[PDB]
Image: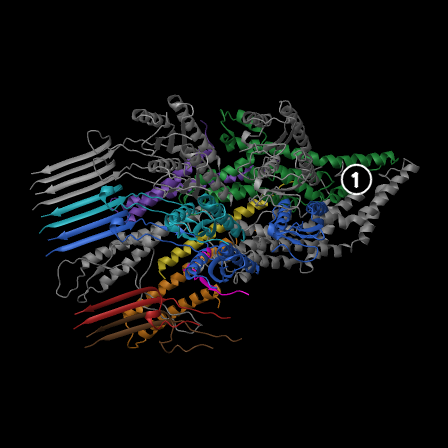
Chain colours: A purple, B blue, E green, F cyan, I yellow, J orange, K brown, L red
């Protein structure tokens, strides 16, 4: 097919969302008392999801700045 | 961009006049329409109206059937217009359209129907003018509402419906017995939305007077009473009342 | 909303941890009273109950709210959690079934898990605030 | 101070949003001279006076499904302030066309990037009308009508009906109508002057309006508009009142039409 | 679905794309071009675009898209509120009425060009065309329509200009500047027939047809 | 509002005519008359029934899942935990009843003499008019037939 | 603008009036269409209508068939017009439309079909006019919706269906024993979406009279009875009801 | 602009009319096309229609096949006109346009078909006019749906299908025995999507009478009944009913 | 009232007010960008 | 009647101040030698007062942040 | 004006919490919290 | 007007929590919370 900016961006945002969801489910099960999951697993995955969130936010800010700079030049 | 609409509507006033006039027992019939008009602010467009005054043929009056005829004429000529709001007047008063008291006329109509039916059924027995009756009708004009939520009882496990059930049993043998049971049911449900009709007969009262031939036989009297009971549509639950008498007329 | 439906679980869990916390500190405080019968609650089952049902705390009534100067007072209130008896070891001649070691290891565990819940809520709320700036 | 308040602090947000929309859009309120903090604080500090006795309870949903509520308030603000701009556009037309009569705008006739006439006569009459507006009850009736919208269209699931943005669209409309009805005497007199000095060309085709006409028409226009300056003071009355009525109408058209 | 993460990224970024992309996606292009062209006739601006014309076009496009916004509301804002429709069927259900709206105004050979230069293969039906191809085609079609409307609006004022110039020059007025004479005549034509209502109504009618 | 009366009159006339059409050849053209009263149910009716079928018997249960734990020691200590996620039949009717049916009919029939008709000759005619009434026992329908000379 | 569509209205009304005259008992027919507006602010789309008044031929009266004929003439001459909106008026009133009751006529048609069929079968046996029948039909005009979700019972482990299973068995020998089991199933399923018809026969009442030749033979009566049961489509379950009698006519 | 398509309409009316005029039993064709507008305020866009009242040649009726001929000619010469949307009327009455009781029509058609087939077969056996029969058919018009989702059973381990299996077997020798067993099966399946038809027969009740030769013999009558069972398409599961009798005619 | 309840309420309200303000900022910016074009 | 949440903030500040003043006067009385007052009671009340004061400080910080943010919307 | 609900025979309660606790050296305890609804007349 | 719900035989309850205990030297306890709903007439 083609690079599919819309489809690619959608897939990336889905990756962010499902990493957050996996971290949240793990923390849910840990605080509910379900055996297995270790504490360091919970903290490490939560921080990984937070870093993914921050990377997405920074990408968004840069792209929004680019779009608003391009759509302001007088033609 | 404004006056042309008023001019058109008045032209249509003339047009409707010429239709309703050219109908036989009419010589002139002038109307005024009631429509939202271009204020540039009104957007709701309340229900319109159409007031007609008609000067009929001298020596003639228009029957209710043709009153409804012309009302539906002018109602179907104007878009988005309920025929009820079209209001017709004779050449001198006497609103032949009925558009707080109509319930009186409706009750009178019900009573007339019943009483005329009684007369029609009993004329063969006793004669044309030998029996008279009057009907009193109790009509219920309250806007009733209803919403029933029958469920079916599932106390009987043989008729219950378990979506999910957890059952924990424990015992040691000096016996220590334990039995934890959790049940989630699915329930049978019924939803009626009853909206009783406005103007139903809640109670009737009918008195029948019959002429003599000398009095009638007892059995001829009781069968007369049974037929008039029938022609009332007599219902004991509606509190209906019926009383019949015989005596010489005058 | 949909802000207090995603943060609801950790909020409820952390409040339940605090409630179990004062239950355990009531165990500790009554260490040497006779016939105390140490209490405790099941955290997982109670948390599921809270999520499905709500709070529905049982027993509590405040006074009315008339014009000022009418001395507010309140009745004795208690959370709807059903206190469970802790199965004792080592009978002790005075009914007191409060074992320091059990109560204290449970106290430390509950403290640590309360701190974990605080960390999780802090992370989620910082994430929300990082989106919105 | 908890959410026992901090969701009752949801009582301020919607009325604040509507007041802020009106302020950012209104004729006098939304002038670039005012420091932005003054306009914002005026919005907050009006809603604080109006917020009690406004029974409002909604929810700023995450991924707001109630943003269509926020829309509503913004829209109503756009209804009230922006419409009041029509009254100025009118004069900003009228005076402009007056210049288009005398000599001032033949640059805008046959061709450019410079218009140069907006600074000349439109800004005379537009700020004259600015003062005429303020001097009443100019600044205030807009705010009172906003409070009236709070009481007639407070907060709802049916915020805006169709057939009601045409009212404001084909409203002006009266921009052209009133701009003319103001500038008509001046235009007619300068039409007489232009046609007269043109008739001079019949005696001699050398008379060259470029040489004769423009100095005459400029003096005629200046003197005449000096003589017909007071005529604006009654007109502005009209120019505001009717537009208020329109707003009033739509503000009172909306509740019985919902 | 998305998880308190991306939701309120895609929303705030969509609000960022609003003024340009979403406003030039629907309307307010045709209306604004026609209004500017009408301002070219009748002489000078005399209508403060930063203050009046843009807001008038904004109100007019609100009116114009009342049906599509109503259908979007019915298809999404009822179901998507709290139950059974979550941002995947909501997206296509809410895309359908806007997409039908745009496809109903697009010239049937704009899409041809933009498919033939996007190297898109066969497009099975009218619904098969993607927004990628639908956006520039809709913009080009709307520019064509705006220029047509502006030309028709220019017709009568051009007629007035030429007839006034002809009268002046025939009656002997050798070298009078007919523009200043014509401008009030332009106003008279535009107000006596109640021109603004005619214009906004004709635009509104022609916009969906 | 009043057209209810018109519709009821039409129904009653229809039944009257059909009764005459059946009965006249038995007795003659003018030897009988009938009259009808129709209670017409003009109330707007909506209904919704959501019957489930009972899965009480494991012989007719439909399980999606089942966790089963059985434990025991031998001082015999036995334990048995069990979880069952069932799955259930469901039947959802939405019967929006028609407006304007007959809830009750009362009909009286009068027959002339040839001298009265005999007992069989009466029971058959009354059964015929019952049959032509659409006579419904669950509708509380009512029938009264009498024999006597006319005027 | 707006004068052009009004002129189109007038042109079309005149056209219909012009070309209605070529219909026989027509000498003037004045008509008006009614389309409210091509809106912008409502999705309700209040329906257009049409009203016509006509003057019939003296000496000729008009069937109902030609009533519907002119109505559909108009309603298909102008689209966007269901025939109910068409309202025809005679040269003097006489509403030719009732603009809820088509049920009575439809029941009449069903009963006429069945009654005629009974006649056609029974006529050869006893003669052309030695028999009469009339039929009463109960018609279920109520709208029905339905959905059934039958499942197969997976009680029988041999006929059950398994997607997953964890089965943990242990024991020690003082015998300690454990057995933990999990079972995820797949289920056979039936899903209808029944949408029952409007206006079906729920109960037919049939009363049959046959003339004499002297009373007909008994087995002749029972075979005629079976014939009328058969042509009736008599179903026991519906509560269908039947009666037959033999007696001389007049 | 729009007057161009208006005249397009008003001229094609003339050309259509002159086409119908060239048929024999025609003199003129009042035709009105009906193109409401191509709106998109609703998802329906009621199909534009057309109405013709034809003045035929006197003394000739226009046959239904030819009625279809002209209706289809109108629906074909005109784009945007389905054949069933055309209305057709005579210069006096005569609704030839029959486009809720369509079920009655269809049922009569079916019963006519099967009844004609019965008569056609039986007439050679017993004579042209010695036999009569009628048919009553129950028809289903309710929209059906069905989605069966059969799964095959894998309860037997001989015919099961495994994606994965974890199996642990342990023992010590006081015999400490363990056996853990996890199985993710995978399952055969069938999924139908039956969407039943509207207008299928559910029950045929058929009554037949045959004249005398004196009565027919036993074997001859039973074979007659068996063949009419044959030609009915009699199905015992459909509850079909069949009754045939013999007697002299009148 | 529970202390953790009070701080969770604090933060929830703070986030909600932040989100509302940011949404209004985006809408106001869009309005001004629309109103600052040439006609 | 009315809540006037500035009045609620005033009530909160008055509560905090009164609690601290009560703890201070109890320490006053105890170190002065007044019989009755116990040491553990003094320390416990001082602890509770400290927690309430940090309550007030945190509310201060978040209110100042909220106000500094509502003064950033452009109008 | 208001009405006197000193009597429980005519008092009208909205809420009433009641705790009774006693041992029998008879230690007794009783608590009774009551919120009332009061009749009223406002003659302006 | 409020109606008197002094008599439980004519009162209406929305909720009621009832603790009853007794040991047997008998140590007994009883807790009872009740929320009512009140008949109410409002003339103006």
The rendered magenta stretch, by its main secondary structure, is classed as loop
Residue D182: percent from the left, percent from the top?
Answer: 76, 50
Q: Which residue is mark 1?
A: E182
Q: Is residue J49 left or right of residue E118?
A: left
- Residue at left 64%, top 59%? D141
- Residue at left 15%, top 54%? B177
Q: Write the start and end of the magenta stretch as one range.
A: B231-250
Whether F28 is drawn above or below B213: the answer is: above
Q: Work out whether residue B112 or residue D235 is closer to the camera in this orientation and state it.
A: B112
- Residue at left 72%, top 38%? E41
Residue I28: percent from the left, percent from the top?
Answer: 55, 48
Whether L32 is drawn above or below I28: the answer is: below
Quarter containing the N terminus of chain E: top left
Residue F136: percent from the left, percent from the top?
Answer: 39, 48
Mark 1 lies on a secondary structure that is helix
Residue D14: percent from the left, percent from the top?
Answer: 52, 55
């Amino acid at each position: 097919s083609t690079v599919s900016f819309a489809g690619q961006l959608h897939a990336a945002l889905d990756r962010i969302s499902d990493r957050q969801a996996a971290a949240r489910v793990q923390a849910e099960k840990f605080t509910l008392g379900e055996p297995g999951i270790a504490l360091n697993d919970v903290m490490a995955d939560m921080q990984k999801a937070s870093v993914s969130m921050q990377m997405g936010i920074q990408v968004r800010n840069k792209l929004v700045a680019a779009y608003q700079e391009v759509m302001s030049m007088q033609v | 961009q404004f006056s042309e609409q008023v001019n058109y509507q008045r032209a249509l006033e003339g047009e409707l006049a010429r239709t309703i006039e050219t109908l036989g027992p009419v010589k002139s019939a002038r109307v005024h329409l009631a429509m939202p008009k271009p204020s540039l602010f009104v957007r709701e467009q309340k229900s319109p109206s159409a007031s007609v005054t008609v000067t009929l043929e001298p020596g003639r009056a228009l029957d209710e059937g043709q009153i409804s005829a012309v009302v539906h004429l002018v109602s179907s000529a104007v878009a988005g217009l309920p025929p009820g709001n079209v209001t017709l007047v004779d050449q001198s008063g006497h609103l032949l359209t009925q558009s707080n008291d109509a319930q009186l006329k409706f009750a009178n109509d019900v009573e007339s129907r019943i009483q005329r039916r009684i007369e029609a059924i009993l004329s063969p027995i006793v004669g044309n003018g030998n029996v008279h009756a009057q009907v009193t009708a109790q009509l219920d004009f309250a806007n009733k509402e209803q919403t029933e939520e029958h469920y079916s009882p599932n106390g009987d496990a043989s008729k219950a419906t378990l979506r999910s059930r957890q059952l924990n049993i424990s015992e040691q043998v000096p016996r220590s017995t334990q039995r934890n049971e959790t049940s989630n049911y699915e329930v049978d449900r019924t939803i009626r939305h009853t909206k009783m009709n406005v103007g139903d007969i809640e109670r009737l009262s009918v008195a029948v007077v019959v002429n003599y031939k000398l009095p009638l036989t007892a059995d001829q009297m009781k069968q007369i009473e049974d037929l008039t009971r029938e022609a009332m549509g007599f219902s004991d639950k509606r509190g209906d009342t019926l009383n019949v008498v015989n005596s010489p007329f005058s | 909303d949909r802000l207090d439906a995603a943060l609801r679980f950790q909020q409820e869990a952390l409040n339940l941890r605090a409630q179990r916390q004062e239950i355990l500190a009531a165990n500790i405080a009554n260490a040497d009273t006779p016939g105390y019968q140490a209490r405790d609650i099941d955290f997982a089952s109670e948390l599921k109950k809270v999520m499905v049902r709500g709070r529905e705390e049982t027993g509590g009534v405040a006074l009315t709210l008339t014009s000022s100067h009418h001395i507010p007072a309140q009745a004795v209130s208690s959370p709807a959690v059903d206190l469970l008896y802790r199965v004792p070891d080592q009978p002790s001649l005075d009914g007191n079934t409060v074992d320091m070691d059990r109560e204290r290891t449970q106290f430390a565990d509950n403290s640590l898990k309360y701190q974990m819940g605080l960390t999780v809520l802090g992370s989620q709320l910082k994430g929300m605030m990082n989106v919105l700036q | 101070t908890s959410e026992q308040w901090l969701y009752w602090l949801h009582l301020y947000f919607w009325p604040l949003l509507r007041v802020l929309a009106l302020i950012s859009t209104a004729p006098i309120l939304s002038e670039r001279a005012i420091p932005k903090r003054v306009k914002l604080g005026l919005g907050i500090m009006i809603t604080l006076v109006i917020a009690p006795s406004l029974p409002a309870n909604d929810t700023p949903l995450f991924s707001i499904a109630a943003l269509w509520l926020a829309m509503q308030q913004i829209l109503i603000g756009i209804a009230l302030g922006f419409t009041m701009q029509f009254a100025f556009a009118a004069v900003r037309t009228a005076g402009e066309f007056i210049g288009l009569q005398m000599g001032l705008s033949f640059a805008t006739f046959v061709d450019p990037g410079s218009h140069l006439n907006m600074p000349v006569l439109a800004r005379i009459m537009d700020m004259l009308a600015m003062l005429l507006f303020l001097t009443f009850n100019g600044h205030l009736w807009l705010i009172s009508l906003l409070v009236d919208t709070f009481h007639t269209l407070p907060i709802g699931s049916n915020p805006v009906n169709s057939n009601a943005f045409m009212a404001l669209a084909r409203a002006g409309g009266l921009i052209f109508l009133n701009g003319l009805m103001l500038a008509l005497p001046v235009i007619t007199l300068l039409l007489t002057l232009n046609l007269a000095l043109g008739l001079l060309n019949r005696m001699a085709p050398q008379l060259s309006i470029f040489v004769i006409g423009f100095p005459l028409t400029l003096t005629v226009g200046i003197m005449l508009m000096a003589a017909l300056m007071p005529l604006i003071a009654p007109f502005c009355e009209h120019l505001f009142s009717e537009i208020f009525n329109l707003l009033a109408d739509i503000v009172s058209e909306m509740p019985i039409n919902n | 679905s998305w998880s308190l993460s991306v939701q309120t990224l895609v929303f705030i970024t969509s609000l960022t794309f609003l003024p340009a992309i979403l406003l030039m996606m629907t309307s307010f292009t045709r209306i604004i071009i026609v209004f500017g062209l009408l301002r070219n006739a009748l002489g000078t601006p005399s209508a403060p675009p930063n203050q009046v014309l843009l807001g008038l076009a904004l109100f007019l496009t609100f009116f114009i898209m009342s049906p599509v916004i109503d259908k979007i509301y019915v298809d999404a804002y009822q179901p998507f509120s709290e139950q059974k429709i979550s941002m995947q069927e909501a997206l296509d259900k809410g895309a359908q009425p806007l997409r039908a709206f745009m496809l109903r105004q697009t010239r049937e050979a704009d899409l041809a060009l933009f498919a033939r230069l996007a190297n898109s293969g066969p497009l099975q039906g009218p619904e098969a065309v993607p927004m990628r191809i639908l956006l520039p085609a809709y913009v080009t079609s709307e520019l064509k329509t705006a220029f047509q409307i502006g030309f028709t609006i220019f017709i009568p004022f051009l007629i007035i200009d030429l007839v006034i110039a002809s009268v002046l020059m025939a009656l002997g007025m050798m070298m009078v500047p007919p523009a200043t004479i014509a401008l009030p005549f332009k106003l008279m034509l535009f107000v006596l027939v109640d021109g603004w209502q005619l214009l906004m109504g004709s635009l509104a009618q022609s916009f969906y047809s």
